[PDB]
Image (spheres, coloured by chain):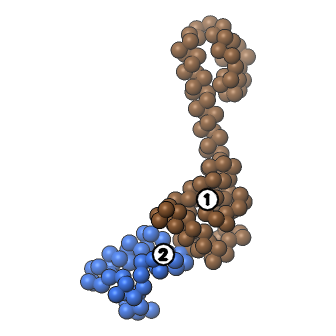
Amino acid sequence: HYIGDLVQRTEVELLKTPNLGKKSLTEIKDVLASRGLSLGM
Amino acid sequence: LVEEGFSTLEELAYVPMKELLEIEGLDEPTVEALRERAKNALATIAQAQEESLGDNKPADDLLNLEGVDRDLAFKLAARGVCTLEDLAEQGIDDLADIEGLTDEKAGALIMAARNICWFG
């Protein structure tokens, strides 16, 4: 629900989620990077 | 070719070279080229049908993901998911309408496909 929940998940965990493609993972990284955040903090 | 009695691509691909060389205006280079084209046409036709349904191309590529039966591979290929890469690129939502595929089973197959394509 929150950005703080998303930032704790690893890239390998997000790829296990249902309806989660490589394209949507790249979108999430690019958007988090635009805000100075990274996956796995 | 039809007046000389050839009706199929198989006849042109496999008939003895002597019978094709008896046709007026065929030389050995043109007969070899005609046979190579006939064999390539036969190969292409087979591959196209095998990718459209689940005969061989999708029965090996799309069916690489552990769990894919031949019926499911043909259902995937009917949606344009012909290869193990095409399946690795899908979401669960893109496969949700396939009769006999639960969201959990779709998720497992996509993850198996990704493990082979992206982490093998």
The residue lying toward the viewer, choosing from A1 and B15, is: B15
Q: Residue at x 38, y 74 (%)?
A: A27
Instruction: Return the residue at label 2.
Output: A15
Q: Is residue A30 left or right of residue A13?
A: left
Q: Residues within 10 Å of mark 1 (few under 14, many from 20)?
A: some
Q: Residues within 10 Å of mark 2 (few under 14, many from 20)?
A: some
Q: Which chain has been coloured brown in this picture? A: B
Amino acid found under the numbered disc labelled 1: Asn
The picture quadrant where one finds residue A26 is bottom left
Q: Secondary structure at mark 1?
A: loop
Residue A21 seen by the camera: yes
Residue A10 x %, y %: 42, 81
- Viewed as shown, does residue B44 lie left or right of A1? right
Question: Would you place residue B16 above or below residue A37 in this image?
Answer: above
Kind of element beneath mark 2: loop
Q: Which chain is blue?
A: A
Q: Residue at x 51, y 66 (%)?
A: B114
Residue in view at x 27 percent, y 79 percent: A34
Q: Which residue is mark 1?
A: B64
Counting from the top left corner in percent of width and height, residue B44 is at 59, 38
* Quarter residue B113 falls in: bottom right
- Total numbered badges shown on the rendered structure: 2
